Length: 49
Length: 44
Length: 49
Image 1: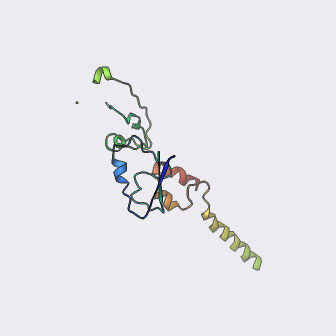
Image 2: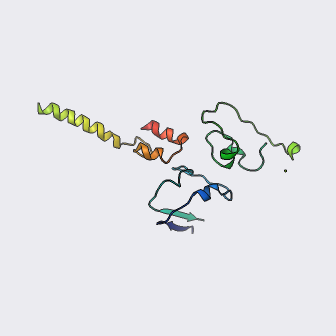
């Protein structure tokens, strides 16, 4: 019953998540983790389970 | 010597804290990487 | 005489329109793939174009 939260209409600082060592794994497909602070997107979905 | 996780990051074109701040390989690296546990010898 | 100008115009038009093809790249605009992939992975996409 995985949850889906929608993320939009805000400024998202991905650098905190990239630099934070609390994450055991952070693997990204399609786009580079180091430039996400630069790109702009339509909407973002977080499927959590 | 490297201890803990991220031991696999020692490789060309890899990302992470170790690869970014500790040991960075070139993109066209031509060589071999060797690793083995050494608890008996290295175990602040 | 109209046919030669028509044929050259058609050749140029298709040559231009071939820039909208991706040939299997994640995108057809070279700038955005360079501006979202780090070079180790972006080279692979650029080669196809």
